[PDB]
Image: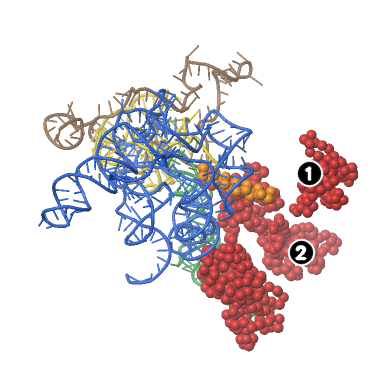
Chain colours: A orange, B red, C yellow, D brown, E blue, F green
RNA sequence: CCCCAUGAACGAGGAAUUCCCAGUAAGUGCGGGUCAUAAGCUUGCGUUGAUUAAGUCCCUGCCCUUUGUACACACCGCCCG
RNA sequence: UCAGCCACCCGAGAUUGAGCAAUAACAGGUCUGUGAUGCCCUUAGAUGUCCGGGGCUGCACGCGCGCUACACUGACUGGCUC
RNA sequence: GCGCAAGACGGACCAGAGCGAAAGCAUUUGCCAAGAAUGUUUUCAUUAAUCAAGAACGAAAGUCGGAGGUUCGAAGACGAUCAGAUACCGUCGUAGUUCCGACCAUAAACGAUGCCGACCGGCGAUGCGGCGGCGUUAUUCCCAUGACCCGCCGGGCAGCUUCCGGGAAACCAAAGUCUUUGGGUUCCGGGGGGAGUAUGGUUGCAAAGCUGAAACUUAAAGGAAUUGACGGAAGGGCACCACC
RNA sequence: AGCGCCGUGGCGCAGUGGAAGCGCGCAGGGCUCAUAACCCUGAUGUCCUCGGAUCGAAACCGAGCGGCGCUACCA
C-alpha cells in the first residue's frame, strides 16, 4: 500500500541521514 | 512494608503543579540540600511518574520514579527515600547505629527493638518520635534500612530498653530493593614502523600474508580501541607508497609485489555480560544411611561431593576395623553397611566388598543432586539429575506447528530475552507462557518448526554443551 | 436340510441421521434373477392397512433479479511484505 | 372476474404410477462386458492355456447397507378360511 | 434531589440553502472595517485579459515558548478473543485536543474538470435585488410598508429533460462550436518500474518541504464498458434425497 | 520458634461415614467434502506414612515426614 511505503521510505531516509552525517 | 513481592496496578505521569507540590513536600521533609540535589535527581526537563502498587494485604503504595530510578515511596502519608537514593545522598536523614545481632533480623524486615541500640557497639543520637531515619551499623558503612521512630531517643535510653524503638519500613534486599528500577622521518617512521610492524606481526595484525599496506595503515585498531597512532604516510619522506615499500622491503622485514589491478601487495618476513556458568554434582544423605554418616557429622539432608563420600566411607571402614587383614582391597561388612548399601538377596550372602563396589554402592544409594554457580551469585542447590533444556514440537490448530522450549531458567536464561532474540532470528511470532507443573515456570513458544535455529542459538551463541539440550533429532535440519 | 440336546448377548438403544403424504407408511408371506444344491441380497407381487400435513424458506441444496469484483485454468481464484 | 384458485353436485374417475427426456458440459465410472481399441509390456523355464491342490471366507480392530428381536396388540398348541 | 466549579461544545431549527480567493464559516447583543449582486439618462475615458521573478492567506497533524487542563485520546498498561493479536472489543491513560504568541506550507486542499470572452434547445424549482400585477391577510375605509399569491429582468447554488453536438465509453448543455483542425493566455504529460529514490543546491529549531537524475529492468502496466463465475452482499424461489 | 493448611487420578481439586468422583488432559468417534476447534462417548489413585479410635471412613486422635502458607519475629 502507498501510504506505508512512503512512510517506510521516510524511515529509511532518516536512517541514511543518520549513518551519513556531515561529519563524514 | 515491602517484605513481600508486590505487583504494580498502574503508572501515572504527573502534571506540573502536582510535581511542584511533591517537591515542596520533599524540601519540607529533608533539608533544602534536597532541592539542591533535586535538580540532579528530579530534572525539570524529564518525565515524572508515580507507580501505584497493591500490596498482598490490600494497601495502596506509591513509588515516585524519574528516569527509571525509584526515588521516594509513600503510604497515604509522608515520602520515604529508597535505600539506593539514600546511599547516594546519606545526609538527608538522621542516622542510628544498631547492635550486630539485630542486623541479620534487620535485613529480615523486623522492627528495631530498644535493647539493640544501647548495647556498647550501638550508638543513639537525638531524634523525635515520627522522624525518618537511616539504620546503620558499626561494621557496615551504608544504611541497611529506612525506618521511623516509635519512641524519642531519650525515652529509648531511659526506659530500660523495652518495646519498639524504630519501625522498619524499608530494608536491604527486600522487594523494593530487588525491583531497583521501573521499566620528521625519525619520529614519524619510528612511531609508524613501530606500531605498524607490531600491527604487521601478531593477529589480527596478520603474521605473514600477502596484503595491501593501505588496509594496514587504516587498520589502526587493536582490541576494540585505536592505537592512538593516527598518521598518514604523507607525513613520511616517501611521497609514494612504492618508495615506502622500497625502504621497508630493504630492511629484511617485508617482501613486495604489485597486483595486476595495481594495488601494492606486501608479504612480511616472519623475522556487561559473559557466558560463564559453573555446574557441580552433589549427593544428598537419605534417612536409611544416616547411621553410616553419624561419625562424619552429616545427617539426613546434608549435601556432599563424591570426594567427601569416598573419604567418609574409607574413614568408616578404617575406624571400625573393617579392612580385611590378608587383603587390603576388601572391606568386611558390619550390620550398618549390610543394612544400608546391600540388597535383599545379598542380605546374608556377601560378607565382603572391594573398595570399588563399596564406594559405587554407597554413591548410588545416596539421593542425586547438583549445585549451580551462576557467576556473581551464591551457589543454588537442587535435587535430582541436572534438568536439560527441553525442546518439544507440537501440532496445534489446523496444520499450525509450534516449538516449545522449557527449563531455560534452570540455566539462568531469561525467557523474555531469549524470546526476543529468537523472534529476530527465526522471524516469526514468539510468546512466553506459563509451563506445566512447577509453580511460576515459563516456557517459550515459537511459531513454526524452528529447532535448527535453537541449535544455532544454544550451541553456537551461548556455547552450551550438547548434553544439556534435549530433542534435537526431531529437527527439520542440523543447522 | 433335519432330530435331540447346548441354550449366550439383548431390559426399546447416547451424539447424530435416513426414508416417507393414501391402497401410501408399516406388518406379512409369495414369484423371478443368481441356481448342480442355495436367499439374511435383489427385482417384482398381492394381502392387512394408518397417525399427520395440504404449509414454510429456519436448516440444507440448487435455481433466477439487483448489486460489487484487481477473479476468467473462474474463491481449491488472485495477491502483499 | 384474466389466468386460474376454493367448496359442492352429477360421476367409475375432479391428485394412476412408471418410460422416454433439451442446449450444453464433467479431463465422473468403464482396457475387467465386447473378434470394440491407440500405445506399453509379455511372448516357449510365457503375464498363454490347461491339470491338481490351497486362496478371495482368514481376525486384537474401526466404518457401512441388511436381517432378528427385546414379549400380554405376545410366544406356544390345535381349529376355520384368503 | 438540592446547590457549586471548571473547561469544552453550540444540538433540534439545518436544506443538494447562504457567504468567502481557498482553507473554511451557525447562541444573544454592540462596536470595527470590508464585499458580491442589484438600481442608476452619475463620473473617469481604454485605465483592460492571463501571468516567469517576487509576494499574501493556507485544514488536520506536527514544533517551540507561554497559560489551561472537561471530554475524547496516539504512546504506554492491563483484560479478553485468538493456534498466534504487540489488532478489531473493553477498563485505565501520556503527548495532544482548548486559548495566546512564534514556526511549518503539506491533503482524495476533488467538480479528480486552469482563467477571461463569444455563440448554441427547452423546463420547472430556488437564493438575492429590481420591475409590474387582480386577490387575500397585519381585522373591516386611504396610502405606506411587511407576509402569501401571478409573472418579467440580471446575477448566483443546483436540478430535470433532449438524436445540440461531442466522446474510448461511463457520461457531459459543457467535457459542445475539432482533419470543415487557429478568440487570448498560464501551468503541465510522453509505456510501466527503478523513484519523487541518489546527489548537489536551497528553506526549517526539528519532522520535512521545493528543485530533482542515471545505471538497470520490463511487454505490457492501465481506462471504460460486456458476458461469465464467485461474495462471509441485498432480494426473491423451489424440494419430505430441506424442515415443519 | 510455633500455629494452622496440606498432602485425592497424568494436572489441579470436591467429597456433612457402608466407602471415590468433578473439571481439564489422553484413546475414540458425531457435525462439515475432510481435519481443527465444537459436541458425544472409553477410561483414569495404599487418599502423606506410622500406629489409634470408629460396628466400619480421605473425612475423626496422636508420633512424625516434608512442604506450603500463616505468622508476628523481644532474635
Q: Quadrant of the N terminus of chain B?
A: bottom right
Numbered circles on residues, count? 2
Q: Which mark is residue B23?
A: none
Picture quarter containing residue B441?
Answer: bottom right
- On the rendered structure, is E191 left or right of B284? left
Q: Say which residue appears at 83% left-offset and 40% top-offset.
A: B242
* Secondary structure beneath label 2: helix
Relative image position of residue B453 (x, y in whole percent): 64, 46
Q: Are marks 1 and 2 on the same chain?
A: yes
Residue depicted at x 52% and y 70%:
B59
Q: Residue furthest right?
A: B251
Residue B79 vs residue C70: left or right?
right
Residue at 59% x, 56% y: name it.
B442
State the residue in front, B365 or D3.
Answer: D3
Residue nearest the observer in this picture, E169 or B238: B238
Mark 1: which secondary structure? helix
Q: Tell me where residue F60 appears, x and y as whole percent.
A: 51, 72
Question: What is the CA distance from the residue labelled 1 to the residue labelled 2?
Answer: 62 Å
Q: Is residue B235 visible?
A: yes
- Horizontally, residue B167 falls left or right of residue E45, namely right
Q: Which of the labelled discs sits on residue B214, or is there none?
A: 1
Q: Position of residue E27 (x, y in %)?
A: 33, 59
Place residue B272 in its image quadrant: bottom right
Query: Which of disc 2 and disc 1 is earlier in sequence?
Result: 1
> Front-most of B292 and E125?
E125
Query: Residue B369 falls in which quadrant of the image?
Result: bottom right
To which residue does mark 2 refer?
B308
Q: Relative to A22, is B121 above or below? A: below
Task: Write the residue at 86% across / 49% down.
Answer: B185
Amino acid at each position: 500500500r502507498a501510504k506505508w511505503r512512503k512512510k517506510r521510505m521516510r524511515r529509511l531516509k532518516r536512517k541514511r541521514r543518520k549513518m551519513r552525517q556531515r561529519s563524514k | 512494608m515491602f517484605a513481600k513481592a508486590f505487583r504494580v496496578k498502574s503508572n501515572t505521569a504527573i502534571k506540573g503543579s502536582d510535581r511542584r507540590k511533591l517537591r515542596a513536600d520533599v524540601t519540607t521533609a529533608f533539608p533544602t540540600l534536597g532541592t539542591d540535589q533535586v535538580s540532579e535527581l528530579v530534572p525539570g526537563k524529564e518525565e515524572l511518574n508515580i507507580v501505584k502498587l497493591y500490596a498482598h494485604k490490600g494497601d495502596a503504595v506509591t513509588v515516585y520514579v524519574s528516569g527509571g530510578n525509584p526515588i521516594l515511596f509513600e503510604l497515604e502519608k509522608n515520602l520515604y527515600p529508597t535505600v539506593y537514593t539514600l546511599w547516594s545522598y546519606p545526609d538527608l536523614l538522621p542516622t542510628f547505629t544498631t547492635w550486630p545481632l539485630v542486623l541479620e533480623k534487620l535485613v529480615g524486615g523486623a522492627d528495631l527493638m530498644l535493647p539493640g541500640l544501647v548495647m556498647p557497639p550501638a550508638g543513639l543520637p537525638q531524634v523525635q518520635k515520627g522522624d525518618l531515619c537511616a539504620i546503620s551499623l558499626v561494621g557496615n558503612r551504608a544504611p541497611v534500612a529506612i525506618g521511623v521512630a516509635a519512641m524519642s531517643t531519650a525515652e529509648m535510653l531511659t526506659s530500660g530498653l523495652k518495646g519498639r524503638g524504630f519501625s522498619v519500613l524499608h530494608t536491604y534486599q527486600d522487594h523494593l530493593w530487588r525491583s531497583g528500577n521501573k521499566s620528521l622521518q625519525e619520529q614519524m617512521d619510528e612511531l609508524l614502523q613501530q606500531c605498524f610492524l607490531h600491527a604487521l606481526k601478531c593477529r589480527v595484525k596478520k603474521a605473514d600474508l600477502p596484503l595491501l599496506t593501505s588496509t594496514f595503515l587504516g587498520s589502526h585498531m587493536f582490541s576494540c580501541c585505536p592505537e592512538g597512532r593516527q598518521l598518514d604516510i604523507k607525513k613520511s619522506s616517501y611521497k609514494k607508497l612504492s618508495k615506502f615499500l622500497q625502504q621497508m622491503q630493504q630492511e629484511q622485514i617485508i617482501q613486495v609485489k604489485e597486483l595486476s589491478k595495481g594495488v601494492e601487495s606486501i608479504v612480511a618476513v616472519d623475522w556487561q555480560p559473559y557466558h560463564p556458568p559453573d555446574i557441580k554434582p552433589l549427593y544428598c544423605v537419605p534417612a536409611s544411611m544416616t547411621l553410616l554418616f553419624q561419625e562424619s557429622g552429616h545427617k539426613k539432608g546434608s549435601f556432599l561431593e563424591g570426594s567427601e563420600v569416598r573419604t567418609i566411607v574409607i574413614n568408616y571402614a578404617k575406624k571400625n576395623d573393617l579392612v580385611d587383614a590378608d587383603n587390603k582391597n576388601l572391606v568386611r561388612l558390619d550390620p550398618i553397611l549390610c543394612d544400608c548399601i546391600l540388597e535383599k538377596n545379598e542380605q546374608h550372602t556377601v560378607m565382603k566388598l572391594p573398595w570399588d563396589s563399596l564406594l559405587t554402592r554407597c554413591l548410588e544409594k545416596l539421593q542425586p543432586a547438583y549445585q549451580v554457580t551462576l557467576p556473581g551469585q551464591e551457589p543454588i542447590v537442587k535435587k535430582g539429575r541436572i534438568c536439560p533444556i527441553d525442546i518439544t514440537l507440537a501440532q496445534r490448530a489446523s496444520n499450525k506447528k509450534v516449538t516449545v522450549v522449557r527449563n531455560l531458567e534452570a540455566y539462568g536464561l531469561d525467557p523474555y530475552s531469549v524470546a526476543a532474540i529468537l523472534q529476530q532470528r527465526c522471524q516469526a511470532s514468539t510468546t512466553v507462557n506459563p509451563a506445566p507443573g512447577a509453580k511460576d515456570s515459563l516456557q517459550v513458544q515459537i511459531q513454526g518448526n524452528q529447532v535448527h535455529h535453537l541449535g544455532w542459538l544454544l550451541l553456537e551463541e551461548y556455547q552450551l554443551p550438547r548434553k544439556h539440550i534435549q530433542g534435537l533429532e526431531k529437527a527439520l535440519k542440523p543447522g
